[PDB]
Image (cartoon, rainbow over all chains, first blue to last red; front, side, top):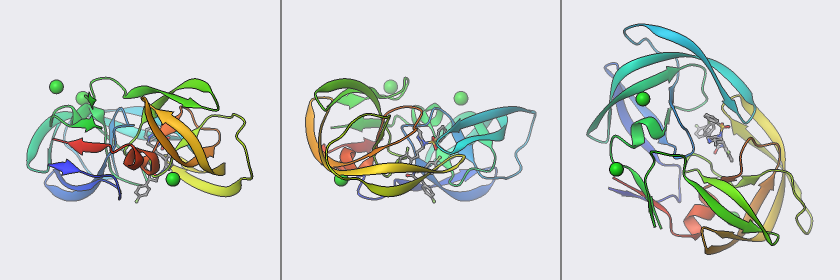
Amino acid sequence: PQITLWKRPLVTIKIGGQLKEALLDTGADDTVIEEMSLPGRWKPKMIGGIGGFIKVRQYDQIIIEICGHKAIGTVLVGPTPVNIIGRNLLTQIGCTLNF
Amino acid sequence: PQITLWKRPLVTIKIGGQLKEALLDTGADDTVIEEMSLPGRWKPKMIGGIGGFIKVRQYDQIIIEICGHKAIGTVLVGPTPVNIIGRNLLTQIGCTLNF
Ligand SMILES: C[C@H]1CN(S(=O)(=O)c2ccccc2)[C@@H](CCc2c(F)cccc2NC(=O)CC(c2ccc(F)cc2)c2ccc(F)cc2)CN1
Ligand SMILES: [Cl-]
Ligand SMILES: [Cl-]
Ligand SMILES: [Cl-]
């Protein structure tokens, strides 16, 4: 698909058996999801920018379905104000910026 | 151009006759640049990031060139960690997300 940017590019995703809304963010290196349970090992990480930093749990090798496209990668879980799909997963679905 | 997301989507911008590097960010509603002098009056604005809200200065109808494409619009100035081109200007240059 082609997504315009008149409004926030929010899409439905499937992660850990749950349907969630997430923002496609070209300006995020990593994917960050609001508090939820995920399987496997995790390690702590700090991520931040505007308004400072937050502590998150880093889970590796997590499968996500974004607009019918399956992708696998690291997912950070923590107190983010919005679910964010970062470049680590946007590359896997072949997402590009065009102008 | 078509920009892939294996690296951060950093481009050259020109604002106030100066070249700067900025990130194309589909996850940002607005454009925010690091401290610099802009003409005219400014208005107060709060923007929310991953860690909370920050105060910035809102300047309107500012001329800015993004990757060679001319735009004229709102530019926020504040303590952002990187210069960010948000949807207000990405729409002006005809930027879309495609997969
Ligand atoms: C370059 C980084 C800079 N920041 S970040 O927080 O520092 C960060 C740094 C490292 C990792 C993750 C995030 C982000 C954009 C922030 C931003 C601007 F920069 C300029 C102008 C506006 C805004 N904010 C929004 O538009 C609100 C919006 C939002 C998106 C991401 C977010 F995290 C927090 C909030 C939103 C809120 C609620 C909701 F329901 C839906 C969407 C992402 N790109
Ligand atoms: Cl990854
Ligand atoms: Cl590619
Ligand atoms: Cl604008």
